Image (spheres, coloured by chain):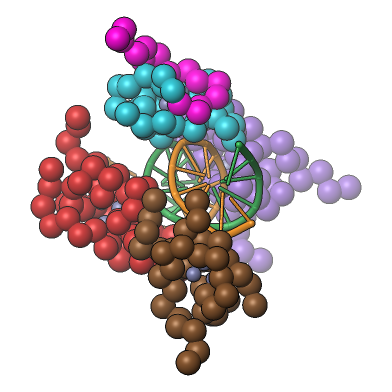
Chain colours: A purple, B brown, C red, D cyan, E green, F orange
Amino acid sequence: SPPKPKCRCGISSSNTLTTCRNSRCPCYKSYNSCAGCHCVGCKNPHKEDYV
Amino acid sequence: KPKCRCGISSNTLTTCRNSRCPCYKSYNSCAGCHCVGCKNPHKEDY
Amino acid sequence: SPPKPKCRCGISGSSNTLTTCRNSRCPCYKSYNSCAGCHCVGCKNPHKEDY
Amino acid sequence: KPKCRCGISSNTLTTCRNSRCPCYKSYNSCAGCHCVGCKNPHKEDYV
DNA sequence: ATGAGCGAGATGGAT
DNA sequence: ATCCATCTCGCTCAT
Ligand SMILES: [Zn+2]
Ligand SMILES: [Zn+2]
Ligand SMILES: [Zn+2]
Ligand SMILES: [Zn+2]
Ligand SMILES: [Zn+2]
Ligand SMILES: [Zn+2]
Ligand SMILES: [Zn+2]
Ligand SMILES: [Zn+2]
Ligand SMILES: [Zn+2]
Ligand SMILES: [Zn+2]
Ligand SMILES: [Zn+2]
Ligand SMILES: [Zn+2]
């Protein structure tokens, strides 16, 4: 299985209220968390709580 | 089959020659249509 | 009035291409200007020169 | 002068106060426009 | 009159 | 720093 694709959202100045919570974030889009990512001001709600 | 109303109500070059004309869109002529200043390139069949 | 604008007309996959840069939504055509410096595709702007 | 239709999908703080409003972009007021929730600061002079 | 569909522009993750 | 796929949202025009 390919390595978990890390994101870099919000690094640059963009709208900080949606960083990693829209379809441009590959993690958010794939229902993953940003564990291990290099995003800044991450607003990803996903926890990978697969239970 | 459609009878369009293009040009009745501006880009005069595209009248019945763009996706919003139901006849152009469907590869049809404007035979029987109510269009004004029709530019449909598909002529009524002789 | 500012220096003439730059457009990006025609980048979408539209088949409505007869009037690319030759209708009111092109800021160049609308202002009686050429597409000098633009990144439009399939440009039909009839203006060869600015102003 | 143009007649814009801004405000008639989201973000109303900036309607007619951003580069996509032909009036704001050209330093014109929205007097006579069809815009709605207009935030254009430019005011039309007195005739 | 009017609103669906259009399409040029803004955005910002990736580079 | 720009680039371009994706999204926004002002504009046109058949209805
Ligand atoms: Zn992200
Ligand atoms: Zn991430
Ligand atoms: Zn994140
Ligand atoms: Zn027609
Ligand atoms: Zn027709
Ligand atoms: Zn016709
Ligand atoms: Zn153009
Ligand atoms: Zn141009
Ligand atoms: Zn052009
Ligand atoms: Zn406006
Ligand atoms: Zn206005
Ligand atoms: Zn306004």
Residue at the far right in the pictured view: A51
User: In the rendered image, is residue B20 in sight?
Assistant: no
Name the magenta segment's main secondary structure: loop
Q: Please name whichever residue, A22 or B15, is drawn nearer the observer in this view of the structure.
A: B15
Q: Which residues are magenta?
A: D33-47
How far across and down, in percent of the image, does residue B21 sit? 53, 66
- Residue at image position (63%, 72%) is B2
Residue that protrudes farthest toward the bottom in the picture: B46
Tell which of B11 and B8 is nearer to you. B8
Near-viewer residue (C41 or A5): C41
Q: From the viewer's side, name the closer residue of A11 and D45.
A: D45
Asked whether the viewer can see residue A19, the reply is yes
Q: Is residue D12 magenta?
A: no
Please state the horizontal and vertical placement of residue C22, each as a whole percent of the image: 30, 56
Q: Is residue A16 above or below residue A39?
A: above
Report the residue at 34% width, 53% height from top.
C23
- Residue drawn at (37%, 19%) of the image: D29
- Residue B23, picture quadrant: bottom right
In the picture provided, is C51 more to the left or to the right than D1?
Answer: left
Q: Residue at x 27, y 62 (%)?
A: C43
Q: Which corner quadrant holds the N terminus of chain A? A: bottom right
State left or right for residue D5 relative to residue D9: left
Total marks drawn? 0
Residue C18 place in picture, x, y as percent: 36, 66
Q: Is residue D41 magenta?
A: yes
Horizontal and vertical percent for residue B34? 55, 66
Place residue D42 in its image quadrant: top left
User: Is residue B25 depicted above or below B9 in this figure?
Assistant: below
